[PDB]
Image: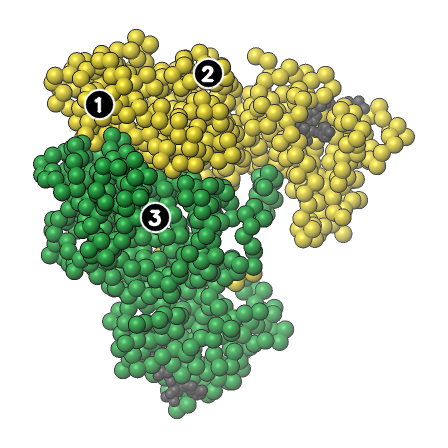
Chain colours: A green, B yellow
Amino acid sequence: QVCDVFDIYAICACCKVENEVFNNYTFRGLGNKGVLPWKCISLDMKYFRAVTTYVNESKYEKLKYKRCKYLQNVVVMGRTNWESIPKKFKPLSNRINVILSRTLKKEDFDEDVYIINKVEDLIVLLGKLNYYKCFILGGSVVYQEFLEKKLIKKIYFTRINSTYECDVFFPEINENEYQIISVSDVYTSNNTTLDFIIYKKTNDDEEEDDFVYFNFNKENKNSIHPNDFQIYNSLKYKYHPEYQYLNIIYDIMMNGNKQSDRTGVGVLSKFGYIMKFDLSQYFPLLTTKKLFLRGIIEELLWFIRGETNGNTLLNKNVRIWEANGTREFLDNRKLFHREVNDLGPIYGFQWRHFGAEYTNMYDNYENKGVDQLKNIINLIKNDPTSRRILLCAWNVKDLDQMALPPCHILCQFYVFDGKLSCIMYQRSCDLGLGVPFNIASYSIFTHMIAQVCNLQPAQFIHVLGNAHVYNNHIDSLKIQLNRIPYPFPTLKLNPDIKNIEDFTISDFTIQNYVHHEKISMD
Amino acid sequence: QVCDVFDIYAICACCKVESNEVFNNYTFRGLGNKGVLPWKCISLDMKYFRAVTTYVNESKYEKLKYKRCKYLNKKLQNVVVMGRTNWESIPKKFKPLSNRINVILSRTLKKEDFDEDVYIINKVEDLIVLLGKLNYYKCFILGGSVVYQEFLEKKLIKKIYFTRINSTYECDVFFPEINENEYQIISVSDVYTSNNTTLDFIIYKKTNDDEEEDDFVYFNFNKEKNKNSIHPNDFQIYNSLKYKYHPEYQYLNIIYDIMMNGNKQSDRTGVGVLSKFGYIMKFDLSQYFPLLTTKKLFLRGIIEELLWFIRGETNGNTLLNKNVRIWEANGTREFLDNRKLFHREVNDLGPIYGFQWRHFGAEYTNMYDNYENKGVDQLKNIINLIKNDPTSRRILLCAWNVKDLDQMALPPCHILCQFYVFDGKLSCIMYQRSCDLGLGVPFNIASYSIFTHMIAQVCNLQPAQFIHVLGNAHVYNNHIDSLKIQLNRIPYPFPTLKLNPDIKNIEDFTISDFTIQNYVHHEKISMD
Ligand SMILES: NC(=O)C1=CN([C@@H]2O[C@H](COP(=O)(O)OP(=O)(O)OC[C@H]3O[C@@H](n4cnc5c(N)ncnc54)[C@H](OP(=O)(O)O)[C@@H]3O)[C@@H](O)[C@H]2O)C=CC1
Ligand SMILES: NC(=O)C1=CN([C@@H]2O[C@H](COP(=O)(O)OP(=O)(O)OC[C@H]3O[C@@H](n4cnc5c(N)ncnc54)[C@H](OP(=O)(O)O)[C@@H]3O)[C@@H](O)[C@H]2O)C=CC1
Ligand SMILES: CC1(C)N=C(N)N=C(N)N1OCC(=O)Nc1ccc(Cl)cc1
Ligand SMILES: CC1(C)N=C(N)N=C(N)N1OCC(=O)Nc1ccc(Cl)cc1
């Protein structure tokens, strides 16, 4: 077939167009009033250059022998495509420029800028040329025709995670026809998140042996099947940061230790992982399922206030600590003399009054115990190279007084070149229900500390101790692993807020959260 | 020449031989004894030996057929060549060597004196002709000391697949001293345990759908002007190695990442460091004791410090009486005064590790006080949780008592240990807030690895993984030159730690209960 012989790839960038279900079709905005919808997105413009111009001559011979039996790249436009280009660069910095037009003759441009009559008249032009691969730069109509006539092999699709006004749309790529094989890292250019995905059309080596020898010792470990991680295992490149979470699910499903827990439900457990997310480039809110952030933002505001009063949350319908405050739960904890929803000296108490004698959840503790939250802020502002900037919730003395010991042991902060990174160490991690919320919680926290100290957020680093998947979560997580992440949203904090204690729920906005549908983890 | 055409490799296994000791690669030279191998079974070596000498790649032969047929002007199996003593050492049940074309060098023996499917040759020359007239993938020289010596001398070996057996045995025959101009190490395996010995595998080399490979180049359009440009020529050896699979490269490779990508900061003193934030190292304590080999470390001091922790001691005088100076400088009048501890006796280090491990929450008085049944005995508690509730996810030991930080001589570097139990095996995560890669971390790895052994043993479990999480990971700028020397040293197989096994209680350990066996190490380095 033609499209493997000649190497015809599309290359596009689609934004979003003016509750809401998402799918790949979400991204389709191509152009507007003859120009791109967006002002300038220089990373995608840079990606464009690299992909279209790149050449590898050592693999061209293998192309030259197959192509005949039937150096630079070919780039195909349409008139309104060729036109919209600002003058001062045409032809495009050393590529074989080419235009599909009806009312343009090849006379009135160069002899390098080969015009074509119809679509069928391009196969003519290639068999007579010396080029690497063929990139359809597109236009609405150009893409429509080249796709309709199964001419396109791979599709270099840039997903622009922001909404714009559009007069022209990329066609609904048929997912039984084509399918995503690679997803890139997520990036911020020009005040939008984006990523780079790849649709394919469906069907010394001294040291290569040395590799096999070194593997001479390697070991259905768990009852988890091959055919079920199909989409997941059928991607080549999985560089989207959400794969850091998803790959831990995979590792624990594939290689996890079978274990009883206190409940009895059954878990697969491993011990010791890292996740790093770049807060300067995205907000890591998992996209492979709907997540809600009001509760966990209220939880955080509750911590910062020093509250241990489970009821302040329940009245706002944030039920994160409901189970941990019942008579039945406190009694099983031997807390027979503790009022319902008095969670004892937990996070907020420890952050504001570590070392103070806990009484009940209504006492006045002003200026009692160590106000660690205040202390790490001053340190961040006054001593940013300090290696002593820890917020520790694990107070050994008070563990037995807490409804439960802190799942999140400590935050350590690091400062370089006006930038703040944070490590949270988590002793116990429910990968299915908990961890996705936990990533969002401390990322927001990392932003909040960043802002009130006049620093840019850099890296949130999540260290998992006991990392477990509930046996009764495995079906749901199987559905989830075979979803492909969307580009992440962004967090906008109200910039007026300059002390850690002044954030209200209103001061938090999530933007461009494009997500798969909800999953009952049960 | 002749070695590249015919792919003539050597494979051997060498132990240390009967002899304030210095170590080079000539340390590992012992090949056999009284006609046989110096050791009974080392199964993991024997299995490696079989995988390498029987592995062929069907698809790769075609190009080797071409290459070899070109030079002569013209199931798949490997050839294996052995001296007559070598051949006679093999038991009947395993002769001839399975799934391989056996060749034997001999003058005293001819075909008539063998029942078995084997080629006999009396000349090295005759082998090269034999190889010319045969279909094989790779030709491996199984040795005998004499066979090894002459195939080397004749510049015939492309690569030596070399097992370092990190134990000592009576030996009568030795591998030839390899000329380091002739052969350079290009690969070093993971370290392992088999039949009560560590070993690794190193490869010496001689000197003098391709559509989705393009997709890689694309997904890198946005990479590096790489921060601190320190010079290539400096890390020549470190960067030459193709496979760096020795667990010591986990430490070494962090030194490199900090040197090449580290952030420049001036610190607590007004000195100078390079820093990054957030690393993890994993060390399989069932397989080796990860005491670093690219320089000398003594453990006496750090074992004394750990026994001093477990006792709940805060008294620096106890360590100085044992001539352990690890805490001396944090105990001086000058230092306690600069930490505002004006009312603190010299060498009274206040409520640090030991105090927090046995008495967390008790009011610190002075280092002489009897704190019995005051504060939470964390160490006792976690020893009980590991014994009675092994799946508990709360087996943390914590030194970072927020309330007492200002009363300590300095806050703890080593913040906490979380424990994990599966199938009678104990693993340990240790979170380090502040890590001097240069002096501190080598010792810190040694301390918590010994601790995992101690807890594991007194709880009737087997040590599994020690996991080391680094927060602020930094290199002092005056350590840089010393660390360059170190990164160009090739690790040796790790030693082993023996705990006196009669110790059933965490408090009952003493110095003499600790034996490091087979520490093979490079030369002492002053980071200063
Ligand atoms: N999002 C993205 O990735 C990209 C978007 N754009 C945007 O695309 C928009 C323009 O695209 P859309 O309106 O389709 O414009 P096109 O670039 O598809 O141009 C259409 C013209 O191409 C010619 N043509 C198309 N098909 C044929 C054919 N089958 N035979 C002969 N000639 C043919 C005709 O030229 P004639 O006028 O001679 O009839 C036709 O009018 C602009 O807003 C531009 O900014 C451009 C590139 C990429
Ligand atoms: N640790 C390890 O990796 C290895 C250890 N070994 C051990 O080493 C010892 C055996 O080795 P070592 O005694 O050197 O003896 P070899 O196995 O090298 O035997 C040498 C004999 O083979 C013949 N031979 C060698 N070269 C030639 C030649 N060029 N032309 C004709 N014949 C030749 C001669 O046999 P003839 O006497 O018949 O003339 C010679 O006496 C054993 O203990 C064995 O277990 C062996 C291999 C590997
Ligand atoms: C569609 C293409 C090829 N791919 C990506 N990812 N982004 C685009 N903007 N591309 O448009 C085709 C084209 O002709 N682009 C173009 C627009 C403006 C200038 Cl200045 C140069 C090329
Ligand atoms: C030298 C060699 C091949 N390499 C390693 N790494 N370990 C060894 N023991 N080898 O021995 C050569 C040899 O003659 N081996 C041999 C093979 C089978 C038996 Cl049963 C006994 C010895």
Residue furthest to the right: B112
Task: Give the number of callouts.
Answer: 3
Q: Looking at numbered disc 2 in the image, what kind of residue is underneath it?
A: Ile
Q: Residue at x 60, y 22 (%)?
A: B15
Query: How far across and how far down the image is residue B243, in percent?
Result: 51, 39
Chain ID for label 1?
Answer: B
| Residue holding disc 1 | B362
The chain carrying label 2 is B
Going from N to C along the chain, the mark reached first, 2 or 1, is 1
The answer to whether mark 2 and mark 1 are in CB contact below 8 A is no
Q: Are marks 1 and 3 on the same chain?
A: no
| Residue marked by disc 2 | B503
Does the rendering let one see residue A511? yes
Q: Secondary structure at mark 2?
A: loop
From the image, tell me which residue sits under label 3. A276
| Amino acid residing under circle 1 | Ala
Q: Are marks 3 and 2 on the same chain?
A: no
Q: Check disc 3 and give the amino acid type.
A: Lys
Residue at image position (36%, 79%) is: A169
Give the image location of residue B88, x and y in percent: 78, 25
The C terminus of chain B - image quarter: top left
